[PDB]
């Protein structure tokens, strides 16, 4: 059997299983798409998998290095010297053009992302938050319309809804994946509902087939917040619009803010292009066709940087899967002792963040002791749920919201350090602290 | 008998008069602020003006070059190799830090801008449009509130008002400067008016003392759109908040989108800082104190680029005043012949754009003939007035607006190419075409 | 008229004349060949010459830098940071291939050189000395055969002849160009003559049309030592084989030793290929068809370095012409006073070295005072003529040789610093010292 | 008891026996010379052998890989990522010096090689072939002088002799080591013999004590071709000059061509230094003292590369000895059955190539079936004996040469893949094929 590695999550899992010998005798080709550039250089030779790959020594550079502390996300570790060298090279080409607003690198990155997501239209934006705002306007959202969404996403998700005067309507999450529960969506639909905004939180996809079945009964649009899920196989199959972020701390990021709007719907894509640049007709600066818009296209310079950094995406995603598997397998004893709950390995997760649940009310004690006793930073993405801020909006509108699963899980969740440039010695340091703090 | 060059417009005009021998009674030193870096390196030795400065040869590299065509604003010419070299140098320091959202270059640029503007609080933003939307929300603008503004600015000014649900209320311009007529503001004030939004159009400052006098009577805020007016002496004396743009084609730009909010009002500055990053408390990510916010702070990488490019601001602004003076003196016969009206030299103008008026209905013919017969691109900033776009909004709310001076000037205005790295031979080519087309 | 810049000496002179206004309105495009890469980036935009080029400021970075001493050839100055960044980039590609003997970059550099010289066959070698030795064997030179050559070249030229047991026969140079005098060649031909070996010394071509007329009458081969003359227009038109060197201090260099054999003659090219690699049949390692051979192909790694460095060749050669013209024009007074003789500007010279003659016996005093009094290094390429070394060979075989012009010129020649990364401030320091030492 | 590992072959065998538990009573330390760098880092801590060393897992990364095919010497497998990283690091320091001919890394590598060989003088050259040619000229070889050598070496050995006009005189090999038979040398000496040129073929040393006894009686020089034997204990004890190659596919290589001349004889070292650079006096460029010379010193850039790569030499030599022992032990059945002859383990062999003899005429059958049926490449180093090439020289001078044991062994020899970064799974695949083809 010969498989072409596409650079998405499903084929990364198949490749990992082959590298670890959990596989039938299988052979691999690599697709020559830009998100596979680093993987092809590092792991392939003459379009075949290198025979002498050792994951720990060659991909993770394991050398028994001594580790004394762990930070959750040291941002200097998220960019490699290889990426820097390439970024300097492409900046030497972009800077003399003087093209610093739109330009040819913006168009090229839109084509690359369209090819990678298998979608016809891409509008590269100045942020994922801006992409969401523009996408909501493009489907016709007016002030007062309702948008069904979960209450456990980053603030940007609700903020894009609120900034255009729409109303978040919060629905509880499921019991297995941190994602909006499809079985609770229909009961929140009102005559003001215009959109369902699922979030593919932590890099895991929501159950989109069920959500689309509901949307189609009520003639609702679906805008997917995929800002943490780049690379996830079949992303967007059922969505009207998919939102990406290329923030520098995402699985793929530029060196500043950026994002994208992805869709097969030409009418929505046109309206997104118009709203993302002042309401002007496409390529007609200063001539409005829509009533207003924003200044929200990507910078050409960041698109050039993105075309260099995206070369590392499938390889960095593979490294993330390996780290996730290694946490799951080495922490299983704590789950058998009913002290924690672990995520499961699935083919869609791109492992932007690695959640566990500490049950029996011990999450705060374990988090605090990991730091104070073991010098391990962990974090809680995110520390306050949407309906629990001390804002006038919440106090006037969301005081009767009860989201029982969301609120219970929020007492238990903890995120462990997971970023592709981590050393396995560093993950071992986290693993030993987690074991010791739970003896 | 000594002037210290501050880097602003008044001292640039005084220096140019010295460099041309119009005065010889004065001696110059230059202050060590970052916007003066290039001017000090190029024109001074040991804080004394070089004795052998030839403006044409030393500042404009005049060489009797043979010109064939003129583009209005070729963006490759707006950045110099010295700028590029410095940008590459600073990015080699920034990139290994991985600090691509907030960072220390953001804070340094805020400090440099605050000193240059003599204002206490600076919030560097992701664009001038975002700065304006945030500043309007900071003074409490709610949906339906009215904002008095001219109808001849770039669309961003009205769009920021519309994006947050407020209502532009257009007032006519004066007879002398393209700026809002203070004598027409009071009669547009209603119970719904919350803000006057004057625009310092083309680089020229509005009559802010009179506008403040009206605002105080009616307890209105003033937010100043200064996106074209960086470097203008005494900018912001009377406004609550001043908005800057560092778009790459402004008199000072970065290499992508950026801007700033400038104020002396700590309460406004705090709200602006909160709205510019998701409504979170300052230095407390994930904890909202405002109902929503944007993702609208400057990128640290662009702030780094800004601290390199701003070194050229006073010097490039001096080159602009020299070019503007040259147009005025060499087109005077066309105005003496009542064919055109020229701008006057004033100490506040930074000459972002150079407007003339072609009277007796000839503007279109002159523009077209300059391009077709002389290969000279001129342009009209901006081609459609705010109350004249063919949008649903205009058809619903603005059909009965009549702005007599704005509409008459709009039939006459034409902008001539003016950018600091233009050659004097290029300006001579424009001059010859304008004279020849008016014979 | 439109001219395509080919990257060779004639077009560089035409481009320089245009840049300096010594020609018509002339327009240029640039051939997209590798040796033009840097010129195209630095001087062209949209395949047309940039309008805003100032030679002194943009090409030479003139800034009135203070200079305190001059070295003749500081080797750290012969390689730019831009070249280094590119070399690191291509090394990251070549190193993991493991291909360090012949390989694809060797082949590609042969193709680039073949295109640039307009010759059918190129064998890239481990040095120019090795290229000459192989080429002499390929034409059938046996021990005791004679090779007619000048006596004023680098020792490599004669050494290649001697290393294969052949006999240099020295002929005097002309009175104008430091090159072998065609009118003295015929009288040196004997029954043992097998080759005429003219040297294009200092970057200037010999009179090859006349040398070919003689060679054809006597059915002799011509091998041209062009190791200093890369880029010279029409190089090799009349020669059977042309030898190149890519030593790091040539006008185009790699980062180590390398050279090339260039020819249109397939028989000679095949034998060169075989002699350059152990006498093996082409592509048949370990299978000899010639009696012996050498290990004299280029390293694949150096060929990859060459493909990066050659991008700078036409631009560096243009800088050399400008420096040469500037010496000629600024030292004219000293020739008028009959103190020195200067080279003339010609379309073939690529100005590897810049010779003057100091007459009336003053050369040693001028050289010694330029260093000890003015801190200027000059050099004499080369200090000993071939028939004047203190070796057994000279004592046995060359004691009766009298080369009147070679010997007289050798008492007068002096080479002035000339290399393309020189500052004009540095050349001005040389010019002032030469003027002052000759008052 | 305690052994300090010197980095040579004897100590590697001793260490290997300890790692396998064929010795128990021995403690090891390791010397701090550069060729031990990687072994010390990988196998020692605080200058004591690591306690937990598993040869298969820790040194060969054994992981039950499924093998599909074997190439004899895939050049991409001969350099490691660690080497590449170190090479890029050192070239970032060398490149800005612009020192690409002579320079300080050449001198440092000469020092390192002198210490490793226990010899006083080292001239690092551009290749092993050039080292041999220069060494032959340094001992006074004249055209027509005779050099006794075997007929089964790489063609470079004979070619160096032929290139300077000298005459190879072939002598048969022994019956046990593939080396020149000392008992056949004396009968080949004539009045014209000046040198014995033994070859340490495949990494095995010749019987040098006996050859020196003969050379002294007959007043001959010995130049040892040790181009395949770096690291062999006691190499060159009896030779006048020892020749090394650092070709990239040798046990130690650079990334291009290089080699060395090694001697204790100062007069010979001086003459080698002069001949290697144009015949010039040492450190007096352009002044010849010998009649001619070559352009044959090492490149400073390749010396820098060699100082990085030589760090791996003792460790890579240790892996080779383990592979060779594994072939000997696992193929012994085929030798017991009188199908093949195997090499024997000896303390001097560095196992550059791994020879077996397939007897009863079956060598070609075994080689062809291993490739066609099992996808295993084997090779024959070398396919044509010196006196059998179809050249004019062989037909003129060597048609009556009969070398009975060389010719018989040539019909039986086959080399098995053996390189230090091969997988043990790959060796097992070769083992299984060779056993299966000999059923
Ligand atoms: Na210029
Ligand atoms: Na002849």
Image (cartoon, coloured by chain):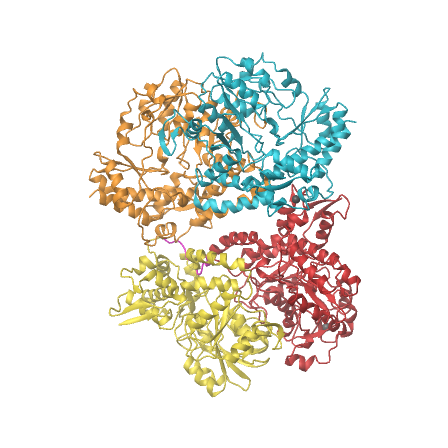
Chain colours: A orange, B cyan, C red, D yellow
**Residue in the foreground of this view, choosing between C64 and D80:** C64
**Residue in the foreground of this view, choosing between D200 and A365:** A365
| Residue C294 vertical position relative to residue D190 in the rendered view, above or below | above
Q: Quadrant of ligand 2?
A: bottom right
- Position of residue D68 in the picture relative to residue A429 (left or right): right
The image position of residue B249, as x and y in percent, is: 58, 34
Q: Residue at x 60, y 59 (%)?
A: C253
Which image quarter holds the C terminus of chain A? top left
Rendered image quadrant of residue D179 = bottom left
Rendered image quadrant of residue B375 = top right
The image position of residue B325, as x and y in percent, is: 69, 33
Q: Is residue D73 magenta?
A: yes
> Magenta stretch?
D66-76
| Residue B249 vertical position relative to residue C148 in the rendered view, above or below | above
Q: Residue at x 36, y 45 (%)?
A: A16
Q: Residue at x 49, y 87 (%)?
A: D218
Which image quarter holds the N terminus of chain A? top left
């Amino acid at each position: 059997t010969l498989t072409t590695i596409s650079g998405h999550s499903k084929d990364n899992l198949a490749l990992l299983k082959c590298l670890q010998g959990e596989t039938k005798e299988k052979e691999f080709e690599i697709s020559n798409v830009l998100p596979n550039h680093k993987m092809k250089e590092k792991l392939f030779r003459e379009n075949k998998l290198k025979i002498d790959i050792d994951i720990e020594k060659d991909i993770f550079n394991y050398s028994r290095k001594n580790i004394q502390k762990i930070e959750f996300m040291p941002v200097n570790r998220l960019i490699s010297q290889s990426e820097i060298d390439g970024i300097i090279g492409t900046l030497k080409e972009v800077l003399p053009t003087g093209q610093f607003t739109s330009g040819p690198f913006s168009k090229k990155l839109e084509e690359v992302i369209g090819d990678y997501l298998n979608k016809k239209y891409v509008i590269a934006t100045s942020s994922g938050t801006d992409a969401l705002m523009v996408s909501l306007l493009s489907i016709g959202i007016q002030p007062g319309d309702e948008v069904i969404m979960p209450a456990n996403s980053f603030a940007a998700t609700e903020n894009a809804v609120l900034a255009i005067g729409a109303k978040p309507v919060f629905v509880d999450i499921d019991h297995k994946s941190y994602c909006i529960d499809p079985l609770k969506i229909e009961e929140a639909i009102t005559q003001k509902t215009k959109c369902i905004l699922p979030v593919h939180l932590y890099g895991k996809q929501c159950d989109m087939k069920r959500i689309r079945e509901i949307a189609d009964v009520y003639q609702l649009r679906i805008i997917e917040d995929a800002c943490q899920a780049i690379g996830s196989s079949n992303l967007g199959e059922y969505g009207d619009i998919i939102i990406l972020s290329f923030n520098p701390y995402k699985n793929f990021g530029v060196c500043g803010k950026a994002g994208a709007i992805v869709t097969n719907n030409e009418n929505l894509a046109i309206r997104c292009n118009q709203y993302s640049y002042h309401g002007f007709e496409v390529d007609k600066k200063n001539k409005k066709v829509l009533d207003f818009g924003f200044n929200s296209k990507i910078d050409n310079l960041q698109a050039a940087i993105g075309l260099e950094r995206i070369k590392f995406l499938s390889y960095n995603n593979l490294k993330r899967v390996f780290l996730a598997q290694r946490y799951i397998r080495n922490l299983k004893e704590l789950e058998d002792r009913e002290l924690i709950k672990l995520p499961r390995m699935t083919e869609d997760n791109v492992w932007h963040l690695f959640p566990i649940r500490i049950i029996n009310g011990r999450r705060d004690e374990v988090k605090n002791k990991l730091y104070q006793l073991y010098n391990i930073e962990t974090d809680i993405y995110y520390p306050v749920l949407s309906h629990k801020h001390n804002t006038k909006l919440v106090k006037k509108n969301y005081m009767q919201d009860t989201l029982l699963n969301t609120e219970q899980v929020h007492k238990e969740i903890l995120h462990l350090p997971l970023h592709p440039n981590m050393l396995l010695e560093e993950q071992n340091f986290v693993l030993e602290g987690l074991i010791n703090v739970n003896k």
